[PDB]
Image (cartoon, rainbow over all chains, first blue to last red; front, top):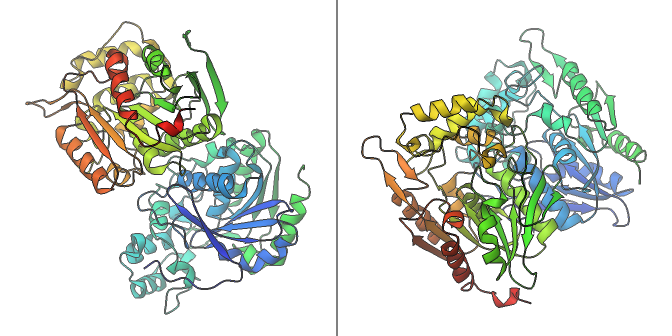
Length: 304
Length: 307
């Protein structure tokens, strides 16, 4: 329907980028440094709603709905990291019109790195990659677990039961397949009787693109990390190896994080790594005060 | 390996790609962005630019993976090509443009009409563009495997991504031996020509393997165009034995392309030039210049873009 939205504590506006009309919320005062917040997959801008007040003390915050999510345009067959990233390049150029710190969670953290490497010159001051699945979200990664061995199971179910643009919509089937899944990474997957608000706002073709290896086909992660041009902060939250299946539970393994750091270091840019092994994947949502402190303290070490 | 040209060249950093280009004419005339064919550098337009600079502010570009522009391993997609050009318009031209492209560049002219930033594109000239026929899974008619694919396969197999194999002699041998009717007229000089020395053959891999437009199905892209389109349709024939398409697109593919654009509610003009060579802008430059100039003069705001 694309008519299922609810109210939020910050006003929302939309901007025509040329193909996507991007929805976003704004917080904070425009005399403060600009901060672009990129949600996790299945998450709308309001994934950041609880933390935006804290960040508004110090930043001019723009939290966006990425294409295929929230009130931003759904674009069948066009889901790629490059299209996600170029939408954001346009958003910075058309809306923000200043250099930004960009912070993103999970797939959004992939896009924060993408911008550090591939944005227009001067657009990106620095990038915060909050529990980003470097390598582990690729179909054939250079290192470690692939998407099939990590976050893939839920993506397969989104595709098979919800379908591209919610064209199947079989939430009841999805829940019963999620409960029956032998993937240990599905063990704590929430299975409410009714689809949650964030999933109702989510184009499940996103999940297809991740599961099928098309989203990053043209953006191998080893190459993209070698092309970053700004300081990078990597936060690395909970992760474990399942002792029955060998699945990666979490965003990326220790080995994948080591390689991501090594590649960035070899590009000659500043890289900082923080391991928070008892934090949840979406620390900006489940521990806003800790996330805000991490981001604010690191941002204060960046050159003006 | 570059050679001299009669228009000075400049480079601009788009962020990932540093784009090389040649500029001619006065900014008092409408801005015109010229996009070469695959394997062609900006100077595919060098013989015709003098004619066009009489009436346009001309920018002829090296697309990523070609000429002096950055080669970008594993990143060759219509979207990445097109977004470079969005950035070029925003950073260099800073005015709305008429965009004219040959072959793959014509695909990218249509791409810009659909997907550029608001207001950047006034109109698109698609000069013998392989709509559908350059897809691996086209909505209509021949796939690339039954059209331009044979040469692309040989580029991949003998020249290699970023010229990493570089077996020009084996390439020529295989071209001569090809069973494809579409290779019958392919030039096989003893040394690689300048345009191909400037070409990253991963371009050919991306077309042959169906990765270049995986995320840009042509039926959907044509349905999203937002500006007037001029389609020129040069020589084409279907081989009666192999069914190969010799040419850029078939009559059936051109019919559907027009129909989809018309259904988008935009102006579309179609000119069939059945005896014209694929690169008319290079091999019949006076004719191409008249087509482009006469058509541009019919566009709304032609007067707004003279100063």
